[PDB]
Image 1 (tube, rainbow, N blue to C red):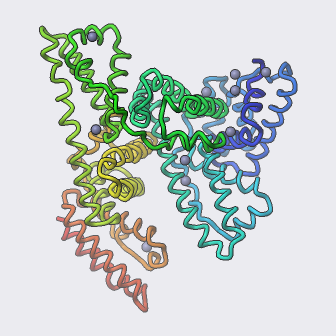
Image 2: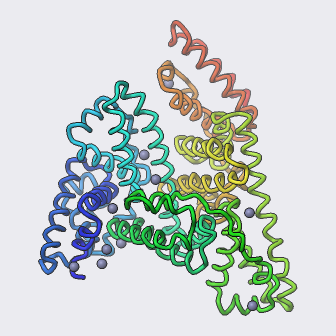
Image 3: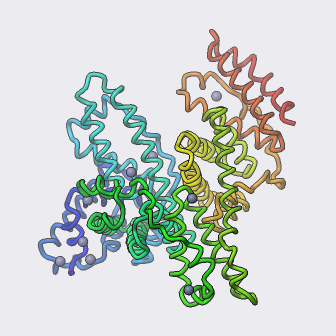
Length: 581
Ligand SMILES: [Zn+2]
Ligand SMILES: [Zn+2]
Ligand SMILES: [Zn+2]
Ligand SMILES: [Zn+2]
Ligand SMILES: [Zn+2]
Ligand SMILES: [Zn+2]
Ligand SMILES: [Zn+2]
Ligand SMILES: [Zn+2]
Ligand SMILES: [Zn+2]
Ligand SMILES: [Zn+2]
């Protein structure tokens, strides 16, 4: 064709086109006001309509990156507000776009979105388009790698939540539990896409492919290797584009893939029926979240092709990519009770066993026991999960989170306290989510979600690097990342942080906060306790923190709260140092 922007506008439709352009620009330029981004969207949209009418018109030929990039580079106060991005604007494509992506900010530290039911219902009623658009903008700048089409889907949930609750009597009671739930899905979804983009960035397209082979094989065990390979190839390109900033392209290709999967759902999975009986946005989303299908009764025995066959070395040499891909496909569809990363470690061990064995005198005898090399790899994460769920079920989320904050602060005491607490708390929510599930679903859930949390830590560490041990675990191997982190002990070369009384001094500020914000304050103190006394046991730390909790409960119950904190605080601060030796 002649004009890409015209083609995108026509296939996607104006609503979704404007939505995706608003998202795209909000992510690149995280600090600009909403009303001003709206004007850039409208200008770009006007251009697209003009081109759609005459594709031969001047500039309609230009690439989407060129058109979007030229637009962002016209923004008022560019050099003052976005000093780093103005530099990018001196460059031509595709350099300019690479430069833009370097400077996306994964921790922009904007205000937390606290919902104001009455004021929001008021702004929703007068102008839904403006209100719904504002939601896209606020989430996108807060999550600069968020999946464009996914955010449009979640914008529709947000709209439905307000459509249900704003006519009702009690607005705040209808709405808050729904918004709190939507927010949990925003956090999860955001972390999932970021891991995909992080994998492209730090490990390449092969790693993303392999991850997707394993996962889609688990979900769609009925599908044959050609079908899984096809979907993976397509899905990889979708996410590559969404991660490279090609949001229109990302959306068009996502829709095509959804159509393909739904045309071939008898061949792919019996669970897709519900998903495929829906409009576009909802269809793609249901497929991405779809439950794993039942194991086929005709799954083939694998020992003959992958352990007993005497020409495996020739198969490995003559067709490395396809023989290994077939193995991962076959083993993954067979194991929905394994984590994706476990499956990837198992494939890596398979490859290594063949490398070793095929260079020796008698290869068949050597690789005969290849499947028995997987056994210890399965045991380690199963033990880790049984152990952590036992602890969670005994002590509950708060104490489990604390235990993890201690565990991780010891691994990396150079990391900032807000980061350690964020990560420890996220790691702790894995228990709440995964330990309740059917027992065969715990390992996949647990490890898959730990991967998301560890990627967050790694992403933060790229920006703010403090620890060579974290660097190594985050960059050496995507499959080995969780076991790498687990194997880290107390960093012995860390110099204990100097004591500062104010760090451990509480005040009546704390009493008025909601529960989770009080917890974060206490959990920050705990982190700092570990930094001061890194060799102190988790049992010593739990006791000391308990004594701080008791102190806070008492003085928040006091008639004179300030005097209580002032009399009692310093004694507790002094005594705490002696309890952590
Ligand atoms: Zn055309
Ligand atoms: Zn095209
Ligand atoms: Zn198209
Ligand atoms: Zn659409
Ligand atoms: Zn958010
Ligand atoms: Zn979602
Ligand atoms: Zn691109
Ligand atoms: Zn053979
Ligand atoms: Zn299994
Ligand atoms: Zn305070």
